[PDB]
Length: 30
Ligand SMILES: O=C1c2ccccc2C(=O)c2cc(S(=O)(=O)O)ccc21
Ligand SMILES: [Zn+2]
Image (cartoon, rainbow, N blue to C red; front, side, top):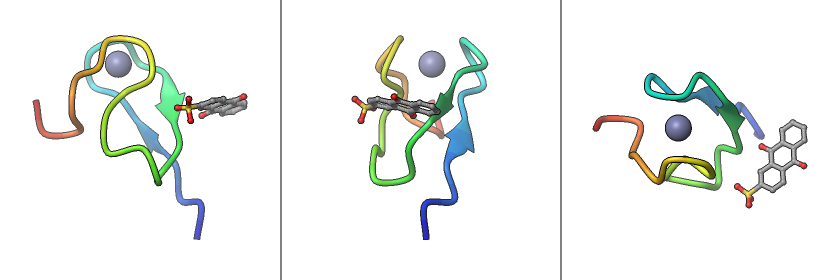
């Protein structure tokens, strides 16, 4: 299940395996 997620900081789709964003490092809940 690669239900990737969209950061709420830089708006970049990051993989699901990645708990943190791969641009600003901000967690999905931060
Ligand atoms: O090439 C990538 C890509 C391409 C098209 C859509 C999404 C991604 C992606 O999330 C990604 C993350 C990462 S990671 O370092 O966050 O795992 C590396 C590469 C990609
Ligand atoms: Zn981000």
